[PDB]
Image: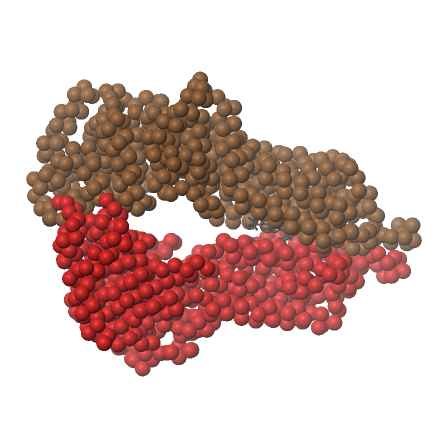
Chain colours: A brown, B red
Amino acid sequence: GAVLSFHNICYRVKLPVEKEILSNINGIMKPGLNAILGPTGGGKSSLLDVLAARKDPSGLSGDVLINGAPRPANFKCNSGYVVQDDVVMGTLTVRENLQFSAALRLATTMTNHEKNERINRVIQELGLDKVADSKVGTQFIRGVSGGERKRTSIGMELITDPSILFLDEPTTGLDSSTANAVLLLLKRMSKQGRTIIFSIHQPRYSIFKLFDSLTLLASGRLMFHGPAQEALGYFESAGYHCEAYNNPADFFLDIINGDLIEKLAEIYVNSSFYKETKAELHQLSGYTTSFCHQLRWVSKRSFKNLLGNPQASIAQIIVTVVLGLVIGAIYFGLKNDSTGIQNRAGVLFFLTTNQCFSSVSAVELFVVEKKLFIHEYISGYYRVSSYFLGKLLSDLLPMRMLPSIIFTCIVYFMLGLKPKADAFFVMMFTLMMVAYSASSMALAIAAGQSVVSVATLLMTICFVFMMIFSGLLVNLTTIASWLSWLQYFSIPRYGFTALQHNEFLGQNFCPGLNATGNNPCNYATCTGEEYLVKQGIDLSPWGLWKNHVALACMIVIFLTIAYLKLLFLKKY
Amino acid sequence: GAVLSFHNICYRVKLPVEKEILSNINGIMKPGLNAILGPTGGGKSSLLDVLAARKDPSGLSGDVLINGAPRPANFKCNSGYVVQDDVVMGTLTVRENLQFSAALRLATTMTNHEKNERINRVIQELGLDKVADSKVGTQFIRGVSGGERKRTSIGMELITDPSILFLDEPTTGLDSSTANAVLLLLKRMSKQGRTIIFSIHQPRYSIFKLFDSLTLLASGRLMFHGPAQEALGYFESAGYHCEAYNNPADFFLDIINGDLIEKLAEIYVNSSFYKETKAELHQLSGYTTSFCHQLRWVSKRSFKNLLGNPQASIAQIIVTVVLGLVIGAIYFGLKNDSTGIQNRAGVLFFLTTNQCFSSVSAVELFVVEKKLFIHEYISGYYRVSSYFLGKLLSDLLPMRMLPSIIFTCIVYFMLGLKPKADAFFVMMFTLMMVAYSASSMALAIAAGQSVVSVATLLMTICFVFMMIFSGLLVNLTTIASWLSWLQYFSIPRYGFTALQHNEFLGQNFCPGLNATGNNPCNYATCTGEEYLVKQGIDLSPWGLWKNHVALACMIVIFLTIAYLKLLFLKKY
Ligand SMILES: CC(C)C[C@H]1c2[nH]c3cc(OC4CCCC4)ccc3c2C[C@H]2C(=O)N[C@@H](CCC(=O)OC(C)(C)C)C(=O)N21
Ligand SMILES: CC(C)C[C@H]1c2[nH]c3cc(OC4CCCC4)ccc3c2C[C@H]2C(=O)N[C@@H](CCC(=O)OC(C)(C)C)C(=O)N21
């Protein structure tokens, strides 16, 4: 098996206040089962991220060396890593998660039969054969238990057959017998020859008896490294008395807590386990798949997540149908009189600002899947471009095509707007474009963040500063010229101007008029063009289509900003 | 000290699926230190809530009897209880929390000097004298450490000098040496003669050596009850071998988990610790303060929380000032021409719907303080009426007086609305009333819930169904008569109709007119009354003030519904 042998690791971060969180740590990890103990504030998870190259090589100041050689560039694609909180797809089943991982991690050369036999072998080694085709589970659907979720998360990284297998906290978040079952599974894996390296948090003695090698850390300093049976005898030789009926790992943490660390670290420097470790270390020292493949599998997984998550996709269509029927019931039969201007301008304003505010629910998209994106980009399933285009083609495109089609098909013929063939399609296309543009601004603000609330609030602030310049509330010509340049940044202004220019052309709003008051008395606003001029809207068809080309340019700019915020994200 | 002696407790709930979660449990708890162990799904916290009467007496089916007598009605006011997650005020300091608890729990007869000496004695017994006047801590301000938060939460219930002191999970959420310090403090309390009863979760042996009496529970059934030293010897006599270097409490849980419960519970029936327990049990068996006082102290605490939480109170005023300057910059100098109707109706619609949507942030009020309200109502600090009126007088009144005054004083004179003395005050009062009414609907929907998101979403749905019937988007006379009755339920319609009737009276919107087109040609909308009639608004001053009396009636109805949802809440 592999022998991961790290020597003289110094590590430091910038919080810019610079601080070392690993001081001077060396150790050898045999084929077998290696554990890392310590407090939460100690460097256990930090050293585990360092050995798997999950933290940046800028702060790292020592050689990490496997089997006599430094770590190659293919190492992250070769060595599996299992996150603390499970990153499995809750809506997909256990076999389709392994199908996804086998499709992206393994080569394109292999047969589907070979990958299916590999998945069957991995799901046989885990004991997930009873639940091989059930869903993993979310809030709405009941699913598989938590220990078998953890076995699924291990089995996703077992597909590529890793030589070294890392594990961040496999015990925590679980109950006791569940944790014992997971660790017995890990011991059955380690007896084969696979080198398991894991960090944990306050284990039991039934856990602690299984360990092959131990590494204790405290406040960034190495406290012990050797065989795990030898550790209690070493701390008896240090002078700390162990009491009867006490867990030795709890005794190890009780040494740290003080019933000092610079006093206790130097005691390990004067050990027999330290000179032997240096005597071993100085002996040793002195993409895969194409683009369309990744886009196809990412889009397939995200669309299957969209189907398997019923409520957040169905309820938007239900509220769209209900609100379309309500707007068809309120504005039913739009007349041509003095109320016609107010009713038509009001319903077009409601439809555009409805599209904008209903596109706030795409903040959720790149924020819920953020840790899964980071883990699967470091583990090397996909590029950022394929993730981005697949998740636009999967979750953004149909869930913004369907509500605008439903709004136009419902509120068009109940209201009785301009009864032409092409005005219907221009209205449908304008609602679709304002939906895409508002949702693209949502993705531009929301991408690369961890919380939903600040991005949602900022979307709503931007929309209430856009709807002032939309054109119904204020007249755009009466804004002062040092402030009227902000009307070009606003998506409802383009959607609403396009709908007003679509609908107000052939209409007359003074019945029985036939020039009674001599082109009626200069204050009438009778024909639709006379309304559409004094709003500041052009009458030429470029005055229609420049709104759509402005929306298309805002879609392109906002999706490019979202892509750059995903690409320039701190992945480590 | 007190001897809490419970006998033959049977307990069951309705989830309506009926299920027993405590089967047949009896035990005696001496003056000293009593611990309750078990799994999470076992009845440890349920039995601890039963003994402190924190669960309803409907499901309870056995006598709980202290010191030879059943529990009186004053018992909850006499025996302290400490919640798992701390319910201390994060923005108040450690001395003012104890001042609050001493003001509400103790009598009105006692001197302020006596209560201050009691607080000094309690804060001396805890070891909080170094941090006696520092703030406890929230997200924005750094504060006291978590163990000293837990000591503060214990000291809040130590004020009334309880004979019996309960504790739900004093170890969890903490680190190891912190938990050992808290439990050594508890042992120093228990040596005085105070009867401490607590539930915990997987303790250490340094914890477990301190116990005076033990009660193990599993799946609703009693597993052991006796002295805690005797428990390991009893389970050796049962036939379960304990291994060396193993925590006995972890061994107790490992017996439960199965390395059955109906097999193992009957073994305790055949004990020597069970017949002795029955031989002891059958021997034994066979507001404070006025209303204005509670309202004053609750309002004082909530106002000090409003000051000590800076950002959520200051940032609303900052965004109000910024948005008032923006609306004063866009709508600057409202002219009297064909654009005057559109600009005035637009800015009045923006102001009213701004008041409505800015009153969504009072959903937070009764939802963040929900567990603190439940704990302090059961422990008996205040009635529901005093809590409700104090938290309306503290957080609702000034944070809705200030933004409406700021909006009116900024956007009034920059826009140049109706330049009178009383129109300014009618506008300020109408914005204040629409703020109160929207926020009262927020309190009516939000009170008695635990999550913020569903209540916030429902507030926003109600507001977007109200702003259609406000009157700018649709004309209210052109709505069909089977659906035009919904316009009376909408708060922006009353605020916006009152502002339009306030501002559109003395205005003329056709310059240089002087009857050129013979009362100009029937389609002009020149004078303000001609606009204000065709919207459906009365011209008499009752057409102004009926909007304000409708807003006052909606304030009264919504605050009454919020009070009934607080009063009829399931407190157990
Ligand atoms: C679809 C609508 C009922 C809710 C939608 C929405 N329209 C708005 C339109 C606005 O214009 C104003 C109307 C008069 C002039 C301007 C202003 C605000 C809004 C909002 C709120 C917004 C939101 O808060 N987010 C999603 C919620 C979708 C959801 O998940 O909720 C269900 C019920 C579970 C499906 C949304 O679509 N709305
Ligand atoms: C204050 C304003 C900028 C945000 C406010 C608000 N106005 C609205 C007005 C609306 O009329 C439409 C205008 C054209 C026709 C109808 C519609 C929606 C809104 C919203 C959103 C709402 C919100 O989502 N939340 C609260 C508190 C937010 C907050 O506390 O923000 C800081 C930055 C932390 C201080 C709010 O104030 N807004």
**Residue A318 vs residue A83: left or right?**
right
Instruction: From the top left corner, tell me how far across and down residue B500 is, in percent.
Output: 70, 63
Q: Is residue B124 above or below residue B471?
A: below
Residue B229 or A22: which is nearer the viewer? B229
Residue at image position (71%, 66%) is B501
**Residue A388 visible at all:** no
Q: Foreground: B100 or A289? A: A289
User: From where the camera sits, is residue A117 visible?
Assistant: yes
Residue at x-position 48% and y-position 26%: A294
Q: Residue at x 27, y 65 (%)?
A: B166
Residue A285 pos. (x, y %): 20, 21
Dividing the picture into quadrants, the one containing residue B291 is bottom left
Instruction: From the viewer's side, name the closer residue of B26 and B554.
Output: B26
Q: Which residue is located at x 52 percent, y 24 percent?
A: A292
Q: Which image quadrant: the N terminus of chain A?
A: top left
Residue B481 percent coordinates (x, y)? 75, 61
Q: Residue furthest top?
A: A109
Report how many numbered discs are placed on residues in the image: 0
Residue B536 at what x, y percent from top left?
Answer: 75, 63
Of residues B59 and A376, the one nearer the viewer is B59
* B424 with respect to A200 (left or right): right
Q: Quadrant of the C terminus of chain A?
A: top left
